[PDB]
Image (cartoon, coloured by chain):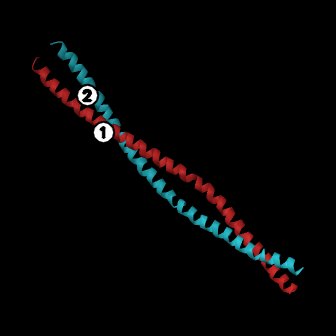
Chain colours: A red, B cyan
Amino acid sequence: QLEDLKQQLQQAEEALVAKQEVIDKLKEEAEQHNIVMETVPVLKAQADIYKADFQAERQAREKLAEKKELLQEQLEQLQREYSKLK
Amino acid sequence: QLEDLKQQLQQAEEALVAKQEVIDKLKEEAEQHNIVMETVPVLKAQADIYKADFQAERQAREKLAEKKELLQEQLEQLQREYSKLK
């Protein structure tokens, strides 16, 4: 009854070495994974900065386009008004 | 002792359940990591699309800003010419 236990205990003792080595591999991979993981909030923040730059630029171009068209009309009307007096 | 051995055997059998779940946790985290990693080429593609649109937008804005400045000078100049005749 004692020898019977002694064998199933040494078997389980080796099975803990077998499982600790699996844990030790997965943990080392986990640290390599984490450094890579650090990059993701950085790429996300970069994508946001480029979207905002584009959106601000687009807004500026549209407003600028409106003013130019407005200026052109004023210039044409004024050229016509001036020609009448010269 | 038979009693000492009994405890050590049920504290090795339970320690294998305790180590398998450490393995099962690390493996489940590994799959959640790989899912976050898949986002990397997506954030990179997004940044590139926005970066290109921003650059195309900046060039159109800079051409529009050159024309608007020219019109403004043409307008202030014509205002000066007109004011001379009243």
Q: Residue at x 36, y 44 (%)?
A: B56
Type of amino acid under label 1? Glu
- Callouts 2 and 1 in the same chain: no
Q: Which mark is residue B71?
A: 2
Say if A32 sits above or below B80 in the image.
Answer: below
Image quarter of the N terminus of chain B: bottom right
Total residue callouts: 2
Q: Quadrant of residue B80?
A: top left
Q: Which mark is residue A14?
A: none
Q: Residue at x 41, y 48 (%)?
A: B50
Label 2's element? helix
Q: Residue at x 38, y 40 (%)?
A: A56
Count neighbours of disc 1 (C-alpha within 10 A) and say few if under 14, some if 14 to 19, many if 20 or more.
Answer: some
Q: Quadrant of residue A54?
A: top left
Q: Position of residue A9 (x, y in %)?
A: 81, 79
Image quarter of the C terminus of chain B: top left
Q: Is residue B38 left or right of residue B7?
A: left
Residue underneath mark 1: A62
Q: Is residue B76 left or right of residue B1?
A: left
Of all chains, the one bearing label 1 is A
Q: Is residue B8 left or right of residue A63?
A: right
Q: Residue at x 32, y 33 (%)?
A: B65
Label 1's element? helix
Q: Give the distance between the C-alpha atoms of the residues marked 2 and 1, in whole angstroms.
A: 17 Å
